[PDB]
Amino acid sequence: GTKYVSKVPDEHGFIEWSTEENLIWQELFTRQIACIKDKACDEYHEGLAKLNLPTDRIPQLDEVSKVLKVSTGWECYPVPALIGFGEFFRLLSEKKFPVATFIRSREEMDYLQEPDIFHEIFGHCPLLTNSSFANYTEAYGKMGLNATKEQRVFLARLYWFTIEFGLLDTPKGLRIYGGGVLSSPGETDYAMNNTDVDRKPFDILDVLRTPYRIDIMQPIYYMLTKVSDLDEIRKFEVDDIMELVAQAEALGLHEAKFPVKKAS
Amino acid sequence: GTKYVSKVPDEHGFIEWSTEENLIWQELFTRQIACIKDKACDEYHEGLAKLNLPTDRIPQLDEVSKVLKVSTGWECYPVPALIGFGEFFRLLSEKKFPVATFIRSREEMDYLQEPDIFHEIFGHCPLLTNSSFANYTEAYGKMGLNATKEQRVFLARLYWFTIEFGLLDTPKGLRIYGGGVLSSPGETDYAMNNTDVDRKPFDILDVLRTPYRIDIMQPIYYMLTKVSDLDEIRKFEVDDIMELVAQAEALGLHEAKFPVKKASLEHHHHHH
Ligand SMILES: [Fe+3]
Ligand SMILES: [Fe+3]
């Protein structure tokens, strides 16, 4: 693998990216924009218009935050390369999106497990300019603040099937809003085109009961009809979310798909 | 149960299986006999007819060995613990097929990573009555006896794509000879039916160059046209095989498919 470390912003929040690091961003950006023109959802494209990201260099977090602040009151928040659940929920609940300030190696161009700066800024930040998606993400952070270990595992699952791997069943066809898909050519092609994979209508109980593995091709995706469908879960009180978590736990998980059974 | 303490044969070689263990065998057998009806290759069905396995209890190793002995000179060889690569090669070179003396728990019915007695007896043993498949397995064991650590990695890759996950491209459609597929409903359905996987004609150099991961749905399969196609590989001298390994290394591995890139690297301490 590779062990990455956040670059430390100077006293102004400035990070000195190298010409090599900018070239890696440029390659990732130009391969992906091409991948998603007719695959990312309309809401995500509108978010790219609002961010107006540089195509040829890694943006300073302040340039992204300026836009997030205008649009939904959010900001990018520089963190170390690994943070715990506690910190993650807390920052989201304060409308601070954690961003580790490193970019992948050349060797790991096609895939890495760690979320790097291209994954966070290209994959997730465009939708944080969308009120529905940003307010949902804020509500998600709140959900986790007083969650037990067991509750946090159900919450991570809701996150996985929405913010990371969410799809839409739109009037113009299947589209993508999950950032895990958006930032990856391999994930985009599989989510859009794989013949046999299960794409199911979103149902919060079904989602909370779905086991998943992070290092396999996903055998199940859930589809909203539009990003604003997240308003329904946004609107639940935390107590309502925990009742749904208690329902999932009491029922136990759905039987795992075969690839999930198999994963180490 | 079978966890923590795998079974040791008594002084007569007899293993006492519980009514629950026998019921697990019966459920595994009945479900698989239905899964492989027109999917397992003819050579495999012929081997089932030779073994006459019991459908409702775990067979004693001797009841299988006695039939392997008369058909191809093979036997089942009980192992109470995973053995090393060196010992695995040595056993195959002696026409001894290692069989772990345990059956999966009920909870693990549909899948377990460690090969159990059902995987070995149902998945592999019917083909060990077939002369082409048996002779190839013996030759494979001979290939590893003086192999280096890296050469053994290439040999395991060859084994994976033949004995474990081999398919046939037949005039009657796609069939299965790999034991990892034959003993699993999930593997059988995916190997026969999944439309996006890459099913390639067998070529030994391609096979030696293909990265793979044990814990994922396989992105690539290799197809013979008949089990007796293994005769071509069996006939090589060990030096010929090591020449092919060196050629593979000179070319380097094929680029990994995306699922292989994504999978967790895993060290295998024991042989498939
Ligand atoms: Fe992400
Ligand atoms: Fe096997």
Image (cartoon, coloured by chain):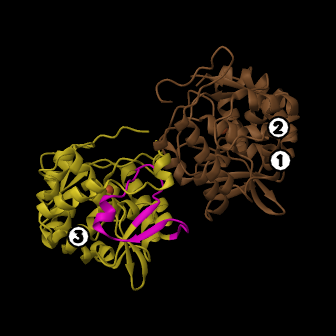
Chain colours: A yellow, B brown
Q: CA distance from mark 2 to mark 3?
A: 61 Å
Q: Nearer the viewer, residue B192 or B78?
A: B78
Q: Residue at x 82, y 32 (%)?
A: B67
Amino acid identity at mark 3: Phe
Q: Which residue is mark 2?
A: B129
Q: Quadrant of ligand 1?
A: bottom left
Residue B46 is labelled as 1
Image vertical order of residue B230 relative to residue A210, above or below: above
Residue A19 is labelled as none
Q: Are marks 2 and 1 on the same chain?
A: yes
Q: Is residue A196 magenta?
A: yes
Q: Nearer the viewer, residue B171 or A43?
A: B171
Q: CA distance from mark 2 to mark 1?
A: 9 Å
**Under tag 1, what secondary structure?**
helix
Q: How many marks?
A: 3
Amino acid identity at mark 2: Thr
Tag 3 subunit: A
Q: Is residue A82 magenta?
A: no
**Under tag 3, what secondary structure?**
helix
Q: Residue at x 17, y 58 (%)?
A: A242
Tag 1 subunit: B
Q: Which residue is mark 3?
A: A133
Q: Is residue A122 visible?
A: no
